[PDB]
Amino acid sequence: GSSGSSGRQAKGKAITKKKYIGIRMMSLTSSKAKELKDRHRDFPDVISGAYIIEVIPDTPAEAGGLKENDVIISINGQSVVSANDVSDVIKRESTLNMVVRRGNEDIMITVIPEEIDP
Image (tube, rainbow, N blue to C red; front, side, top):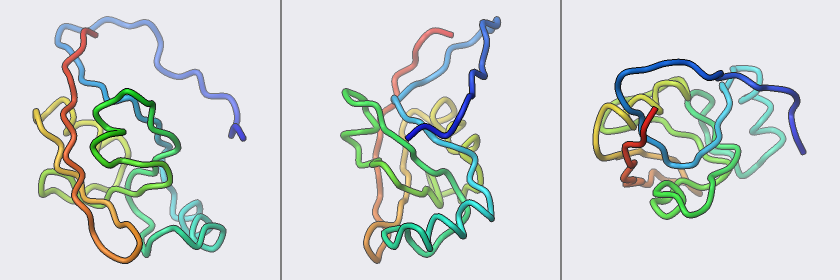
């Protein structure tokens, strides 16, 4: 079930390259999270981070551990509070030491994002 229309990111111009791991996420809100839990018992005891809506297959993120309905609380030893922040570490650092909460504990997700042209 789609959420709506969102055709952001247009043909721009950059100098450096960007990494990719085939993953879709949406800006998590205090109101969205509070409802995500009550609506999804599977949801952890968190409400601040990057919410994964779908992880494209054949990607370094799908095999790493990042699964659908996930919430990143920290990456590379740095706590995140925005899906835009977790995406930065992808191009910032070569490795991706994410930490998502599964079941009732914290699990590390090592992903190797490849540097692709702009």
